[PDB]
Amino acid sequence: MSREEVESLIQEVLEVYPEKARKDRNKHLAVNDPAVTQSKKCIISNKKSQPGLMTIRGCAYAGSKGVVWGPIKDMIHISHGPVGCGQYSRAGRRNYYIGTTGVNAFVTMNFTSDFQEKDIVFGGDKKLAKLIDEVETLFPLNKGISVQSECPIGLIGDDIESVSKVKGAELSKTIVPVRCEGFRGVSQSLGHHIANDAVRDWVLGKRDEDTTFASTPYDVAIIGDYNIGGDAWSSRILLEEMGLRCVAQWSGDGSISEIELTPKVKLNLVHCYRSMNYISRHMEEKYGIPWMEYNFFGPTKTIESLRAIAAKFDESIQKKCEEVIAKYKPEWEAVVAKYRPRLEGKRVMLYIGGLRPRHVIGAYEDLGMEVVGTGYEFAHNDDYDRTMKEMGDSTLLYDDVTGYEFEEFVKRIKPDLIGSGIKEKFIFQKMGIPFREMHSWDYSGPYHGFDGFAIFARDMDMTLNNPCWKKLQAPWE
Amino acid sequence: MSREEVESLIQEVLEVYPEKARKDRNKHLAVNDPAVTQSKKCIISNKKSQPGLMTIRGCAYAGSKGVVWGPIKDMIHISHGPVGCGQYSRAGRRNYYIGTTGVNAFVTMNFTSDFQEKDIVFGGDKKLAKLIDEVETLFPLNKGISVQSECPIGLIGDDIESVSKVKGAELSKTIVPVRCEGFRGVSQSLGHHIANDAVRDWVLGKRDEDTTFASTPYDVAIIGDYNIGGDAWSSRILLEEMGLRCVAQWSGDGSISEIELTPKVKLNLVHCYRSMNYISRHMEEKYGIPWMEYNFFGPTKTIESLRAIAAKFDESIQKKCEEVIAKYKPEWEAVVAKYRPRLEGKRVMLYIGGLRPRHVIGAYEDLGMEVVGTGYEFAHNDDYDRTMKEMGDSTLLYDDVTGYEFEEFVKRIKPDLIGSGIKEKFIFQKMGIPFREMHSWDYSGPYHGFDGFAIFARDMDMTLNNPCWKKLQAPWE
Amino acid sequence: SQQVDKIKASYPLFLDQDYKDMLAKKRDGFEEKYPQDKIDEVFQWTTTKEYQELNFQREALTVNPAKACQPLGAVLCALGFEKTMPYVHGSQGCVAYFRSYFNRHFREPVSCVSDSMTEDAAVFGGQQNMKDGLQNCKATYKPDMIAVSTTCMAEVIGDDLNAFINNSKKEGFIPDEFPVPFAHTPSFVGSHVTGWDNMFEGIARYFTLKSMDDKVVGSNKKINIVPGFETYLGNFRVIKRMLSEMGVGYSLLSDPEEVLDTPADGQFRMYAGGTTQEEMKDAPNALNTVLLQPWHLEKTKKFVEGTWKHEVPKLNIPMGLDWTDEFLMKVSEISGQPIPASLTKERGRLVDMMTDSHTWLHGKRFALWGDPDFVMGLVKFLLELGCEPVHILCHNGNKRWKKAVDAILAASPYGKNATVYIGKDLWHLRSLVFTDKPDFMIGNSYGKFIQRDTLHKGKEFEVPLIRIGFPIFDRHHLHRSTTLGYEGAMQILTTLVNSILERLDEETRGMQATDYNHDLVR
Amino acid sequence: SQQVDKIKASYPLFLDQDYKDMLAKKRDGFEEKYPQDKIDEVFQWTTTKEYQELNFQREALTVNPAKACQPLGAVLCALGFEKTMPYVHGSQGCVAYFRSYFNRHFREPVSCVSDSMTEDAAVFGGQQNMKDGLQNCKATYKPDMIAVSTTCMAEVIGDDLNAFINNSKKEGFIPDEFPVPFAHTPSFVGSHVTGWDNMFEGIARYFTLKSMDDKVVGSNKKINIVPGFETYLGNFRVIKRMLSEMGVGYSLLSDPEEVLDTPADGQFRMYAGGTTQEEMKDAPNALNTVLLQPWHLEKTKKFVEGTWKHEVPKLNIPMGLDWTDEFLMKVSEISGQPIPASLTKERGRLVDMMTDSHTWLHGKRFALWGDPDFVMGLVKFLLELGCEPVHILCHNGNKRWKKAVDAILAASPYGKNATVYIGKDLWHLRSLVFTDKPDFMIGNSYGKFIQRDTLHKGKEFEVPLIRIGFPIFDRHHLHRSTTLGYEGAMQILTTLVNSILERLDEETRGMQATDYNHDLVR
Ligand code: ICS
Ligand code: CLF
Ligand code: CLF
Ligand SMILES: [Fe+3]
């Protein structure tokens, strides 16, 4: 629809809010203009959620434990506090890994101190020390322990840094304290930042004096790919077929040794800028490692990123890049020839957390599909600066959208497909709009690379053209 | 109860029958007297069923195809006629075997000519020849074909003997025609006899001129054990531990070569006299092989049979028999010590086909249990001659019992347990009496030997003392 | 050997070393078994395209059929009526087999009598058998009605059921007013569902043919429901519940749900529930008659349209979403009763389940078999779910039914890889699942062996079986399930999606090998 | 690499040779992985008695808990009321997690709001958050009621819910007559079921504490039903159906079955059904109040007995046969309504199913876990079925509940090998199933990993999981099942016996090895 129609729709959606909430939410909605380079004059992000408005955002514990630290497989992560936060995040995110779950990998397990009233009143530092002792006794093959603080830890005056230092010195083990209490920040973004700082301060600087790792000129690290359904592996296979050596993966299927070996690489390949830009900038400052953002969503973005990455190395890498592109051209061309006719001209509305609302636009456009509305839960204004050019003109932009706002926008816009999280999935399925989970890939995937593009196109076709969407109205009504 | 009370109950039960049916059924009910050696003066058996009275008996096709011929694993058995008889008997009897079911063993498969109207009107001999050709083409590893006639084959003037002879000569394969039409005889007993005659006339005399099989002095065959749940294997392990060589098994887990090798053994061990006495007598007459009946139900009968069998051989076999008995004494003694207290004094009523109503009495008595009523579907008067001594005084005897008769007898007698077939199982479970299937062992077993005795005692305890039998009356009634 | 505290049944008792050695001695000494290499080679050959061609060139041999004979369906239909004894004229072995089959499927008592015709009746006929059987059955089991079908022996001999029953009544063996409907049910024609059709038509004509003068269509404000051959009690219950929810007066003719679900309370009830003779007599007074399974109720439909003058609607089996909708709309149109909000809500909940599960159901390939109406309803529902029914087998199907199913498949893009087979048995289906492997099989318990065969080729070739249909012998209480209506569609959807998820969990349970996809959330 | 016609998702795409080689390079080059021999040795050690002793000496570490926190149960209870918004005072991350948990279990939308307390409220309290949240939620989602629970942050800080709500009403953020019941639900006390209890008691006191003068016990001729924390919709439906069958007037307080089963018809309903405020207000007028799950409704019981003056009967959860009988007899005694013939027939059919399946169910050994009332009902039913619940785990159970379960076990010979564990998590249960292996596990989806672990030791040590309880994430639409009443007992019996038979079929599917026991009929 026209730009003026979008502004009118925004105004009539905001009419029902109280004056303060409406005034706040008016700053978080925008009509896109790709010619604008600064989003601070177009949209406001990374702010408080209005109380009692059904925000989708999570907490800092979700951004630290659930996003950055949890995927690291050889480490044991203690949800420090009451049982709830660890129980609700157990195996809820599909950060795939290879290992033996009771023995040397612990991603899908729930370790928690299970705080009670006595621990709230008298503190849980002694309980934390005893817990670390028991973790050492019962899981001897763990290569490190992280302590992710839940809300009460930051409020009862618990000193987990001192316990971590004492027990780590005593057991000669890495113990990383993370003050990732849920009330800190406004969303999972501050959790990302706190987890990046913890990585920098407790893990990253472990082998600075160590020079026993042989470094090749083609050493790269993958930063900010969490292997959702195997996305990191699908990116790594393409990167290694290009002649590159992927030393580290952050943090999907990641190990603590890979994090400790990252300062030795030649290039950092940052997939999720939002969650790992802090550590990327720290590594560039301290070790002089350049970092670059890349997109492996869809064949066009994949090819562009592969060429951009190969342009950072010698001519042999460029030749191998061209060979990989030529090798994979028939596969994605066949995927397009099969699925683009079934998807051409269909409109999409997206609302994912901090990277994907702009990263997956090219994969949609490669199947003839247009994105008419996008938004973020916890993105910053640099994310919207990157998003505005990737969006078309007069497309809706929403930051920290509320349930009512998103439902009203979908009702007016009427997209052919919605890509969002599990808390919107069944809401929009009941309204008759095909829905794709853009966090967990609807328990499918990967979506990165050419294999991921094949899977993604098949999934979009299987959901958008599903017969069940033509049976919502009873024939007698 | 008293003998007079049992006769009174028989007379009251017979009152509802019409005059002819009552006069007939009065001859098929008796009160046991163990001092009587001739049952023809006490009971009448092997007669017509009264029409429309819900008899439990089957047909001659059931006694031939389902009982004698079907267990032979390396042969393909064609149910010749309409699809029904073969479909209802497919894998319904648990005659266990070892083999590859599509390839070299065919016990649980259903081969049928699937007669239609054209085959009824114009005959099915050409169809039978073409079927045999297709069987040869698609199952090349079969070692023989039997053709079990269903009812219409005996009524449309089909000549399956000529087809069998012609195709067997042409393909150099054993093709056994069995005129086992259901209307022949009165029950499965005539099916047994017809199948025994077919074995004698088409299979048994195959290696009379062959003398390439080395015969030891301890060669025995097992005749009339159909490996129900592994009963034949449990008997064979004890027989071979005694020093004997079991050349053949008839016909559970049996092969055609074992049948052809039976005329070379030194002793025939007949378990089911009813179904295999014909072939045993023929082998004794033609080859001079003695045959003896044995019982492997319960430890007392097992020990008696083992000693009786070992008494037919030299002293080394007797020593091995005593060793086997001493080796297995602790096992069955422990089984008794565990289960007899839970079963002592409990009364049983049995109605099985032709051997088990008298053969399993010792196994019951070995657990402190008494049998107050027994009967047969299709036994002859020799079976009742053997049964009268195994039964106590003033116990009920019924031949070809009707449904109404059996419910009335159970209602008056009120046994603790009933052992019968699947057509009485749920009838008596609804009446609140624990029921054990005495044909298929309730998909359990084996019950032969000492291992079988352990299984049998456990099953009787698990059903007789089940909590579900004390919950049939609602607490508000 | 047995431990008294850990007694082992046949499995795994015979896996013990002594039993294995004894079995190996038996095999090596006397069985003259083929070499294992030869057996493996022949099996591998049986899984091939060449074997499939030879298998599908069969004309005279049937291996593992997927059908039964007419008197079984006649017995079921007769059991559907009140205090009615099924009575099969012919040989007692057939009655024993029918009773055992139904006892194993329903796990409940099944009452049926035979007049025990033997070789003495092979040339003389079974007239005396009929007389004595009718008299004895009435005296002993005291039924209100005796419904007579035939075994193949009586059909081949040529016994006249009408004349035999009339002579039984004329000579006082049974009262002249006692209802004895009859039907010729030749096992060499059709299948068990044909027998159900024949028995129902016989009973309906017995009760209505000579009393049509005072019959007015629509005078009782009811709709007749003829369910056909049905072995799911939930189907009877769901039809009755949906009709009662609409406030629609109905007569369910041949309702055996009560007698097949008798409670265990210390008493055995040979009879329970069933269609009353008053209902059968008043059936021509209904507004219309709806046949739940039209493809095996053709004789009944001819009688109802020609004698009762009921304009029987062209309705598919109320299976899946669209066909249940059509059935409900037709019932509403006939009875004048609107579809209530409860049924609309149930339909919406089924649609919600389909939207919830479409991701795991999409593109899945199924081989399926069963009776014609059930098979085509299942195919329609699978097409509605986005699934692919690649191998559709109906041993008792016909050419017109195949054409109808082909028309259904051609209307959906998910039926483009589907082939319909009529007159083919389960050995044909085994070849098909070896050659064009589906993801799953749907059918009765006889399919389990096919699964075993597939597993013998390898875990990667195993086709798991989903037990929907008749008969199911290796699972308990599945006959209480539902396949009709929205409720049956929900049950089928749950079974299919959870079979898919259970298979995926089994495939991804290997630690450090496949467990990267062993997702907690699916 | 991908074939366009056979696209492969992560499984088995990553089983391809190039992916395997890339993963092996990653492992050997940079992961510094422990040697496979060391990993195997440590796993084998974790399956041992010594590891079990070390595991059960745990005091400060919890691994894989089998419980959640109070505000989850508070949110469920609030969802049980009509047009009621659950409102959690505290941090928004908790609300996101609660919504995701319930969305994954029910596969349905779940509405809940947070006032988004942040670090600015860490020292200042969340009064302004409460005011703005109440105003915004009422303006935006237009609920009839807002039910307030707390996150652990608000509990630790010490926010006064009553004072905050009163100040919100006093300054016009929400109308003074708008119902805002509240409950303190600290995540460090009890578990989610404790939160359900707290929320229900808060709502009941909000609606009845100040209006008891005109209340007469038994003036509306109804029985109050408090279900407790319940995640099976079939349980609500079966309680309502059984009470309607008896003709018993009832009020189901906190009924969320409607809002958790909204139809998909092109419209999203945030609210559907639920207990009305009139029902809550008239609740003291009932004859009595029956608590379906007494072991986590102690605060509600104290309020109902102390304020409503209801002589709350001592009733177990209506699970299994005997306890359903006791529930029905108590309902009959309270309401004066006799138990109808339909319920007696249903009981007889359940008893028939038990007699049909007792052979396959006898002596089977189960390790089970879940909430206290559900666990003890399951244990009682297993004892009724002749099964052996060897490992009974309840993470949120207490000593009195353990004593009650021990008394139940001691009353039956099938509970002699049973041990009850309270305060133990699923790592303890993994040790227990490795050391004293049961035949099966019964519990929520978190048990699947235990099964994987057992399968890693060997197929002969694998303990299959039966998914009964909360939450179930890896199977679809299991939340529609029933566990209460005779219907729930039938469903549980069917699931148990068919799991046993499916396991037996899998164990005997090996051709020429174990297929001698691959019986068609079981
Ligand atoms: S063969 Fe006979 S009816 Fe002897 S037809 Fe029948 S497997 Fe019975 S009492 Mo079923 S004469 Fe065998 C018998 Fe006995 S099928 Fe089995 S149990 S010992
Ligand atoms: S007594 Fe025996 S089982 Fe009966 S027919 Fe005769 S051989 Fe066979 Fe067969 S197809 Fe059906 S079941 Fe019969 S009516 Fe004919
Ligand atoms: S915002 Fe985040 S998820 Fe919330 S508590 Fe805080 S760290 Fe945790 Fe935890 S136990 Fe339950 S879920 Fe909370 S109320 Fe506390
Ligand atoms: Fe849904």
Image (spheres, coloured by chain):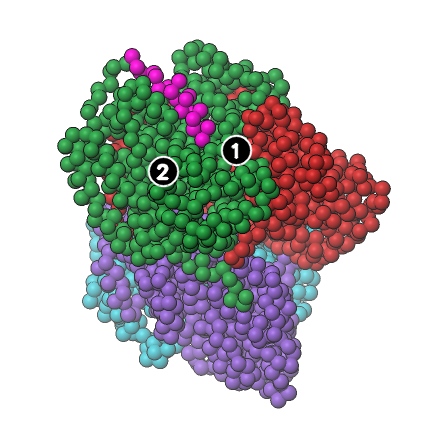
Chain colours: A green, B cyan, C purple, D red
Q: Which residue is mark 2?
A: A37
Residue at the spot 52% in from the left edge and 58% down from the top edge: D265
Residue at the spot 75% in from the left edge and 53% down from the top edge: D249
Number of disc labels:
2
Q: What secondary structure is marked by label 2?
A: loop
Residue at the spot 42% in from the left edge and 78% down from the top edge: C156
| Magenta-span inclusion, residue A204 | yes
Does mark 1 fall on the same chain as mark 2? yes
* Residue C462 as seen in the image, left or right of residue A149: left
- The mark nearer the N terminus, 2 or 1, is 2
Mark 2 vs mark 1, foreground winner is 2
State the mark number for residue A48. 1
| Residue C119: quadrant of the picture | bottom left
Bounds of the magenta segment? A189-209
Residue C440 position within the rendered picture, expressed as x and y whole percent measured from the top left: 37, 54
Res C159 visible: yes
* Residue B91 as seen in the image, left or right of residue A87: left
Q: Quadrant of the N terminus of chain D?
A: top left
Residue D128 position within the rendered picture, expressed as x and y whole percent measured from the top left: 63, 32
Res B35 visible: no
Q: Chain of mark 2?
A: A
